[PDB]
Image: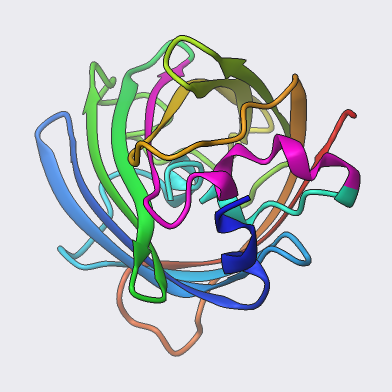
Amino acid sequence: SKGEELFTGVVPILVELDGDVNGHKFSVSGEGEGDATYGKLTLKFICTTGKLPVPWPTLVTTFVQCFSRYPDHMKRHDFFKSAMPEGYVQERTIFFKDDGNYKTRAEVKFEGDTLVNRIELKGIDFKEDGNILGHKLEYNYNSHNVYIMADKQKNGIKVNFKIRHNIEDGSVQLADHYQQNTPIGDGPVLLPDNHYLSTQSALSKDPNEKRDHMVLLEFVTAAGI
């Protein structure tokens, strides 16, 4: 396919987010690199408007699936890379159990040789005293499976999954994800058979960094075929 060749080495990544959660406005910038050969991502995010109003972990999924490692035998199912360099639109709705929801819209594509993820986030109906606004989530992250399916009507894919956020009291905060991706260009893309992505992520901090930020290491590989 098209994009395949674009991912053959380490690619620099730029992440830009504009958000509003219950009237609290904020901006985030992130930079790093991805190496789809190992399904590996390394990023650092910085809250540019000051203190992040929600917990960092809640934004992970929002902050580039084209960096997933697809095994040789599954290359024909890699929609993400097939949409490059023109890119794709990724939209979601994220429902926090017994809490508010996030609505996101992003464009992911290449600007020169940098892979760009530009997002607009809108959060509503959050409880001032819930796990999100109340900042009760631990600073860590779990492994998940992300289910993918073809959408022949929109020439895209539909994706669904649940994230499990650990709460400081030992409990769990569920986050139901509903997602749609559609190509930006008019060129051909690869529509996949049902399959899934297996994820793992580690969160850390930069000891010498005074701004509000998050350091992220993540591995993702496709499976189920």
Residue at 20%, 68% in the rendered image: 48
Residue at 61%, 78% in the rendered image: 10
> Considering depth in this image, is 48 or 186 the residue closer to the camera?
186
Q: Is residue 150 magenta?
A: no
Give the quarter of the image for residue 47. bottom left
Measured from the top left, where is residue 38 in percent x and y? 78, 65
112, above or below 176, in the image: below
> Considering depth in this image, is 34 or 145 the residue closer to the camera?
34
Give the quarter of the image for residue 128. top left
Q: In the shown orientation, is residue 115 left or right of residue 193?
A: left
Measured from the top left, where is residue 202 in percent x and y? 68, 60
Asked if one can make out residue 134 in the rendered structure from this viewpoint, the answer is: yes
Residue at 37%, 51% in the rendered image: 86
123, above or below 186, in the image: above
Q: Which residues are magenta?
A: 73-96
Residue at 90%, 43% in the rendered image: 73
